[PDB]
Length: 57
Image (cartoon, rainbow, N blue to C red; front, side, top):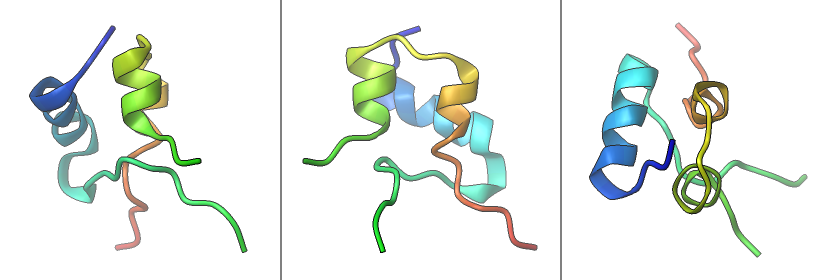
């Protein structure tokens, strides 16, 4: 539920596999990202999944 530090990174590695992840969602045209939603808060797998990089292949 709460995934912090290494455990967060493990989760993202596992869920995102080859794609990679990032920690802050992009914006645009006061920061915040996976830590906030998955570490300070429990988060679910679909939220976690949102910090997987685009595919592209």
